[PDB]
Length: 295
Length: 295
Ligand SMILES: N[C@@H](CCCC[NH3+])C(=O)O
Ligand SMILES: N[C@@H](CCCC[NH3+])C(=O)O
Ligand SMILES: N[C@@H](CCCC[NH3+])C(=O)O
Ligand code: NA
Ligand code: NA
Image 1 (cartoon, rainbow over the protein chains, first blue to last red):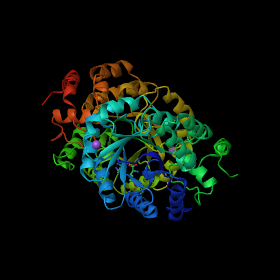
Image 2: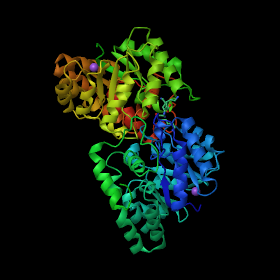
Image 3: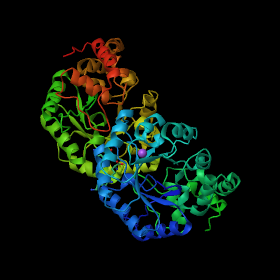
Image 4: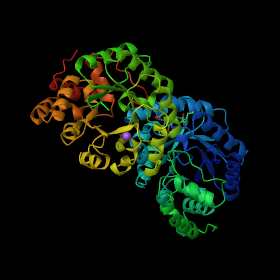
């Protein structure tokens, strides 16, 4: 495909009663279009997939598409830890208008490598939308290694992989086993720029939510081989790459977005909780240092 | 209250079409009654909670209670990584006939300590059935420590905790922070005898699916202070404590039970896969050495 560069793993904004705040979601979409983000992932981990039941999950993906109105690709979150639940989310998104789907490996139940292969083959067989694989063993408790991802490159609608391990040596291992056309996205903001420098195609990012302009600049420059401009853009925002993780994503990034006036309400669904006050100064400082206005 | 000793985290047997095999489920319950098991957990991790949707999950818990006919306590699995979803599962089990519910900590979304407290408090508020907490960081990516668990002891119907860390020093730390009335169950067969000796109340176990008589003996001896008899019973089955984890549980134990003829078929739901041929000889040996008659 040609989906690449700076991709935002969008937060799902909520109202005071915990229902989805569609007005803010629309404003987030316009914001990304204006700021130059390359694509939007709806209902990934950053979008709190776990606490959206299926009907709400697909309503969010569907409305995100509708707000985009052809101006930016939207990629639908479709991972599950039951192969059948993943097919069901896929099928429900077939008619949506989504450029692609992003599916985390099964979490918590720890499938073997052949189970991962069979899981994603079954999900790919249920659609012709492109599928992007997503490895994050720090949350799922399985590390889907390059020699497993490799056995899936042959599926014609499996087009790429979001790897969040921060292990940048995996770019070369993945390039050698998957070819030049398999799309490689960093899911780890802190190593993102290096990950592009070594050969990656793009970044599906948290920090994106709040610094989309500089992040886009960082990414373009790194893809273009202009490393000084890439490091110079990274420099400004780098503190966010730890501060947005003082408590689990998206607890911090949701706080930042509310604090900035991007979304009406800071509400987040249990078992996640609002950023605790002991980290508020830490984050506010990192936001100032990233040139984010207010307060 | 009075649930302690050897508790089996029951496998969920399936037909070769992947539907639930209630004829083998019934046979499993009778077997445990015969062999002296103290209680059954239905739809824990070992029971494939992940790949059972909510209404099958309830069907399994409810049939298990029915087969038990008041002859052995049944504990219902009610963990979820969304608080609302844990509530729904708890509410559906309220009039099933369970003695207790077992709830794993939220997995994959990594809530903070205060989020865990809020989650379990909300879940406990929706029922009058006793609630056992369940910590397994190796699967969930969140480690709920003694200090956090201590703050839930006062909740009147949260009666104890299944810790699967294999960190046996936590028995002492949990006793000191929770008191003597909080029930402490080991979730880790390899350290279960030791966990009992150091003060625990019971074991919620994988191995006792296939060696229930010996595992009970070991638990009874350990609780009664007869460490020689506990150690003699452990010695005979110890091989199973690593052999049953050669792939993620319940992959091996489900293969073992089929191989023994406890269940009609060895089917398991995607993304989980049947035990790999390469481990067959290893587990068959560990089985013979535990005195299981291969059928
Ligand atoms: N909370 C469950 C169900 C999610 C339903 C779709 N977003 C999970 O993380 O798998
Ligand atoms: N596969 C999802 C849904 C579970 C449905 C209830 N057993 C999860 O692991 O949470
Ligand atoms: N996220 C929860 C919401 C509660 C159930 C809605 N009927 C679920 O996955 O089911
Ligand atoms: Na491909
Ligand atoms: Na209590």
